[PDB]
Length: 50
Length: 49
Image (cartoon, rainbow over all chains, first blue to last red; front, top):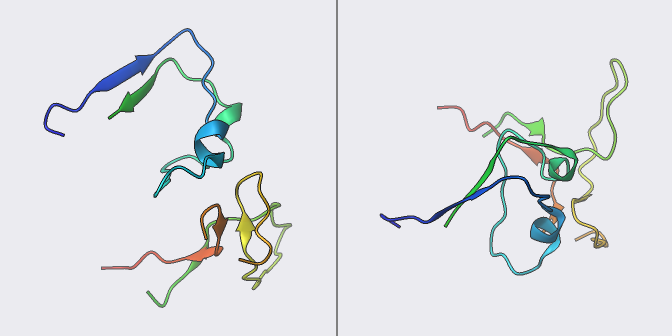
């Protein structure tokens, strides 16, 4: 966690419905955006920090 | 925690509409059957400090 690995996503189509419909996750939360609205949106970049 | 707001609704409120309902909100594609994960209780608190 000190060296947390970031992925930058660009020039690509990113589904969040596979993320929020999956039973696999012990927690799922969102801030500033509705989780149901995510699939309608477009961004310059998307980042995933792991 | 005495103060509350509604976090989810299945449609927008009309002008000066008022809604006390606490029915469970199906956020996923999978049905909730009145009861959890992707099946959320719709009222939440600011927890003011």
